[PDB]
Amino acid sequence: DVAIVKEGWLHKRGEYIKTWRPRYFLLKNDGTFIGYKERPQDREAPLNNFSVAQCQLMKTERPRPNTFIIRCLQWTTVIERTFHVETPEEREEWTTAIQTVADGLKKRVTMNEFEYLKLLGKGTFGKVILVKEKATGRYYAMKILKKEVIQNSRHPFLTALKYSFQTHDRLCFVMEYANGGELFFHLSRERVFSEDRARFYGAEIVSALDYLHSEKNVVYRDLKLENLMLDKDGHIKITDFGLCKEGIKTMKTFCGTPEYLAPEVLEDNDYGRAVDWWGLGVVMYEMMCGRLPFYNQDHEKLFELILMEEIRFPRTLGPEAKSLLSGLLKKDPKQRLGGGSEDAKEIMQHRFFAGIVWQHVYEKKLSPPFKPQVTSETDTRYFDEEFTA
Ligand SMILES: *CCC(=O)Nc1cccc(C(=O)NC2CCN(Cc3ccc(-c4nc5cc[nH]c(=O)c5cc4-c4ccccc4)cc3)CC2)c1
């Protein structure tokens, strides 16, 4: 039943390097809108990252004429993809096709109950906020999004969406906020993790990535050290505090920092589940080596570093760790560990994760190698000022 409704060359604006790139886009009746560097001769499981389901289409003349924007709410994050064609007629042909398929797929808690503590981050369509529920004393991160531009599922290593409510102009997502401290703060304080400790953190991330891939059919895409926290027990919590942010202008405009970006994501080429395995490679590389894989100031260099410079490893690192990182950090997704049809299983069966019972990881049977210094989830120790040191 999966068929191509409309295809052709578009000009997609880079998602991280905001330049225009010619990409051949395939629109399918399942709602997938994928772009490729070259016309593909041709995983098969549809990724919701490219889905046009429940998306509003906007025709703009800024920043470039004949521009149409696809805006989608994915879980709790508003994403935008900006496209450009040569003639207005072409743009109408595309928007009508997309809107048709988007419709073809269509087949009391308030703000006063929380206390504002800290601004975690701000973006184009809203802000993220650290709150403390007055009643329970629990700590949460609240995503306040603009309503204009716009619970049943759970996993032990993902920041759970506790509840969602909306005001007259704002949509709010209340998520669990772990109080075991930022993982980069722990890695910064202890310099390097032992292979055993990194295996623990690594194993829990793999489980959550498998969940997002096989169950939710989604790519996390932003796996980095900054997006990892520990709970009071020292178990990993991958966060969901991301926001759409406009780029910043050496004279070029970039969206975020590239050091963790998979090569196929930098080039705005086709990407899949293999992206998170790169992300896992970067994270695990830093835990066991105490530094980022590629590092250079000039972004022109940093891009090349990720794109062409191949990773080298410390001699004090075990061969089992080498094999894992080497495969995880293959520049080509199809050669990358976990980039096959087996996905996560390709990694769970790796020598580095030998002896690890993967049902035990999911059920948190594994005893954490590190226990945060908190009495309870309400212990505000890792929010305090000595968090500086
Ligand atoms: C305005 C700029 C812009 O939009 N840039 C841009 C362009 C193109 C793509 C992106 C983009 O993908 N941006 C973000 C989107 C959010 N990603 C993080 C993330 C991924 C997945 C989840 C998530 N999704 C779920 C879906 C369905 N059921 C679930 O249970 C889900 C659970 C999660 C989840 C994952 C981890 C922790 C907690 C929940 C959430 C966030 C990063 C890239 C941007």
Image (tube, rainbow, N blue to C red):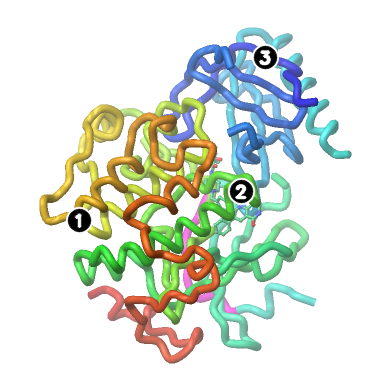
Q: Give the position of the C terminus as an image quadrant.
A: bottom left
Q: Give the position of the N terminus as an image quadrant.
A: top right
Which residue in the protein does label 3 denote?
7
The residue closer to the viewer here, 366 or 149, is: 366
Can residue 215 be seen in this snapshot? yes
| Label 2: element kind | helix
Q: What's the magenta region?
A: 115-123
Task: Kindly report the secondary structure that dominates the magenta region of the rendered protein.
Answer: strand
Q: CA distance from mark 1 to mark 3?
A: 45 Å
Task: Residue lying at the far front in this picture: please name it.
Answer: 355
**287 above or below 250?**
below
Can residue 119 be seen in this snapshot? no
Q: CA distance from mark 2 to mark 3?
A: 27 Å
Residue density around tag 3, few if under 14, some if 14–19, many if 20 or more, within 10 Å: some
Q: Is residue 120 magenta?
A: yes
Quadrant in the picture for residue 92: top right
Disc 3 marks a residue whose amino acid type is Glu
Which residue in the protein does label 2 denote?
214
Q: Position of residue 313 (x, y in %)?
A: 17, 46
Identify the mark nearer the N-term, 1 or 3: 3
Disc 1 marks a residue whose amino acid type is Cys
Identify the mark nearer the N-term, 2 or 3: 3
Residue at left 65%, top 27%?
A: 33
Quadrant in the picture for residue 167: bottom right
| Label 1: element kind | helix
- Nearest to the eye among marks 2 and 3: give it: 2
Disc 2 marks a residue whose amino acid type is Ser
Q: Which mark is residue 289?
A: 1
Residue at left 57%, top 23%?
A: 35
Q: Is residue 2 left or right of residue 175?
A: right
